[PDB]
Image (cartoon, helix red, strand yellow):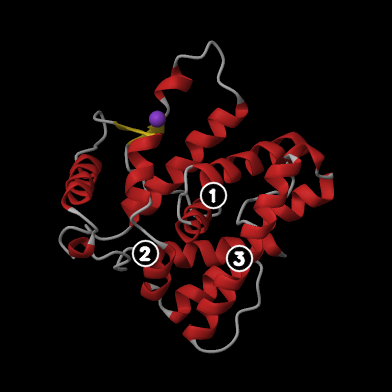
């Protein structure tokens, strides 16, 4: 069962993260980005019980975009790539270079598919196509209502097509719905605009939860400013 595979590979991946170096802080493009990076992590680690830190979607997205696929995939080990492949319902085989190729190949398929779906509208998809679309992108889908599948897929498309959040980081962040209750980071994502709506949509709520999974990955690794 996929659910089975996702629970074990997620839990394993979360273990690996605690000692992974996924980004090189000193190789960040420019000086303004480095200070954003410093501010973000300083803020992250200042959170504590009775001292919850809130992060804007746009605040998180700028940091998230520094964890680029090329660099992240090259930094993942073979066991991490294997677990990541299985989580994405692929059959991993070969050396780490081949695993990277299979994952990249898949992300290209997903890219071509995302364009199609976004142009036609998620509402044009059948129940069965929604289910499959979500599985392929690292999203639950199992036991999930059609409407919720639609909203999940809309969230994925906004973050990928419009916010440009790196897809590998995205997949890794979604493993945090399959643990393994996440280690509390006392941090939370929000959109100022959405917080002023008389009613936030399920989409808006799902968008916050997604950014929260991203924060969860960012709180999982060793302090990037030290390592
Ligand atoms: K925002």
Q: Where is residue 9 in the image (x, y as percent from the top left)?
A: 54, 67
Answer with mark 3 or mark 1, whichever residue precedes in sequence.
3
Of 154 and 120, which appears nearest the observer? 120
Q: Which residue is disc 1 drawn over? A: 177
Counting every numbered tag in the picture gives: 3
Q: Position of residue 119 (x, y in %)?
A: 71, 43
Q: In this view, does 8 lie above or below 127?
A: below
Q: Which residue is disc 2 drawn over? A: 17
Dot label at residue 3? none
* Quadrant holding the N terminus: bottom right
Dot 3 beta carbon under 8 Å from ligand 1? no
Label 2 SS:
helix
Label 1 SS:
helix
Quadrant of the image where one finds ligand 1:
top left
> For the point 47% across and 53% down, which residue is it?
173
* Quadrant holding the C terminus: bottom left
Q: How far apart are marks 3 and 1 (CA)?
A: 24 Å
Q: Distance between the residues labelled 3 and 2?
A: 25 Å
Side of 176 relative to 20 (left or right): right
Q: Which residue is disc 3 drawn over? A: 108
Give the class, few, some or many, for how many residues have Cα within 10 Å of label 3's Cα (few <14, many ≥20): few
Answer with mark 3 or mark 2, whichever residue precedes in sequence.
2
Q: Where is residue 76 in the image (x, y as percent from the top left)?
A: 40, 73
Dot 2 beta carbon under 8 Å from ligand 1? no
Side of 15 relative to 40 (left or right): right
Answer with mark 2 or mark 1, whichever residue precedes in sequence.
2
């Amino acid at each position: 069962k996929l659910i089975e595979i996702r629970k074990k590979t997620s839990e394993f991946l979360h273990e690996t993260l605690e000692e992974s170096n996924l980004i090189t802080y000193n190789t960040i493009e420019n000086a303004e980005k480095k200070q954003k990076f410093l501010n973000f992590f300083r803020k992250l680690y200042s959170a504590k019980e009775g001292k919850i830190m809130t992060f804007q979607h746009d605040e998180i997205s700028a940091i998230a975009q520094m964890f680029k696929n090329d660099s992240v995939l090259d930094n993942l080990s073979r066991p991490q790539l294997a677990a990541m492949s299985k989580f994405m319902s692929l059959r991993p085989f070969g050396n780490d270079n081949m695993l990277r190729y299979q994952i990249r190949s898949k992300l290209k398929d997903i890219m071509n598919d995302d364009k199609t779906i976004d142009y036609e509208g998620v509402e044009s998809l059948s129940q069965e196509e929604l289910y499959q679309a979500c599985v392929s992108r690292g999203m639950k889908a199992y036991g999930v209502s059609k409407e919720d599948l639609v909203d999940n897929l809309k969230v994925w498309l906004e973050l990928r097509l419009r916010q440009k959040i790196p897809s590998v980081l995205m997949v890794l962040s979604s493993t945090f719905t399959f643990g393994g209750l996440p280690k509390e980071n006392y941090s939370k994502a929000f959109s100022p605009l959405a917080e002023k709506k008389e009613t936030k949509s399920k989409y808006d709520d799902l968008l916050d939860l997604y950014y929260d999974g991203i924060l969860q990955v960012l709180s999982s690794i060793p302090d990037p400013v030290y390592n």
